[PDB]
Length: 384
Ligand code: B12
Ligand code: SF4
Ligand code: SF4
Ligand SMILES: [Cl-]
Image (cartoon, rainbow, N blue to C red; front, side):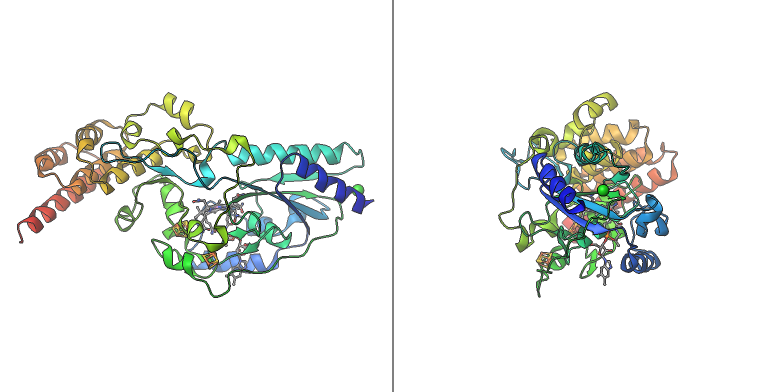
């Protein structure tokens, strides 16, 4: 009965493209509660989490009289077909793998909606509540308890067949499905992810200081702290380094969902056209990927930082125009800093001139920083 329904649900899920499906109870996540409070205490959370901790750890609060949670995962591609080369004259930035193709929020919700209708169609007073990423639960906590994957040292839920390259989602129900068993930790004594993290944001095994994580930092709307400006590289959104160095992801490149295929021209886009992209064009080109959810400003800020990283002198005129003309202080200021960082002394005087016209105090500060960078590199070249 409930066993039959469970088997039928699994078969149906597989037929519509769910790559892994698991079951847990709707019991409280007691371990998670203590962890969330500790992470909060340490200042290690991002701010993208649901703020109400009781809601995050109590499925029965979210859906009254809940009895189970159905967890799903879909594998996403880890290699980009026909990836364009970034060259000296044509530098490109990169979106993380979780922002390739159609927004996973839409894809996984579409699958949950099907699973919900499957259950409701039985006409048995079944009630459900679904979420992907933007709901109250910890999707990883659910996935772990449901046997989808294990919690690895890089904080990823990691599956044996698909590695960590999976999107997660879940559906709370009032059906007393027999729960599954958590699976074995496979990390052993490996520390490759912790060693490779460019900022040391993985402060302990399975412990992220999100405030230092490049993935978080790419998504902030203000000025990027200077210490991270030389660590972001050419990343425009997200960071995949603690996954790509992982042995458990070796040879894991799954292309099972056509709409997830990256479009290289937006997944690995030319940086200079991003500096001058209209709101209309951004919405048309980028509007359906997950990495567009904060709008274009952080992407353009990151594009500026990437050009500074490449020391792309050919971008200097456009950065100079941005410094003067962009209505957003974060863009004007970051452009000024980048002009300094790129290191062409022919632009030092225009920085000095811009300083006296800029009225935003934070943008003014960034122009000062850019002037200082040029002074410092000028002195270094002269052995001073
Ligand atoms: C906030 C957020 C972030 C933050 C913080 C991430 C973090 N590690 O906490 C930032 C912006 C940095 C981020 C980055 C990324 N994220 Co994110 N993010 C979320 C979000 C919205 C909540 C995460 C959260 O609550 N974290 C709080 C921590 C404390 O808990 P948790 O990781 O959820 O749960 C684990 C810990 O509590 C741990 N734990 C519990 N008790 C204890 C005890 C001890 C001793 C220890 C050590 C650990 C421990 O076990 C839990 C289960 O694994 C979720 C969606 C959701 N609603 O859950 C997506 C989610 C975690 N993100 C996801 C993705 C894909 C990413 C990126 C890979 C994107 C990218 N390419 O840049 C990176 C990965 C960074 C990393 N190494 O973790 C996926 C991960 C899927 C998977 N297979 O694991 C999720 C589930 C979204 C989804 N539905 O697909 N993200
Ligand atoms: S996503 Fe990048 S910055 Fe964040 S923990 Fe992983 S490797 Fe470090
Ligand atoms: S790199 Fe090593 S320690 Fe890190 S998640 Fe992969 S197997 Fe675990
Ligand atoms: Cl039932």
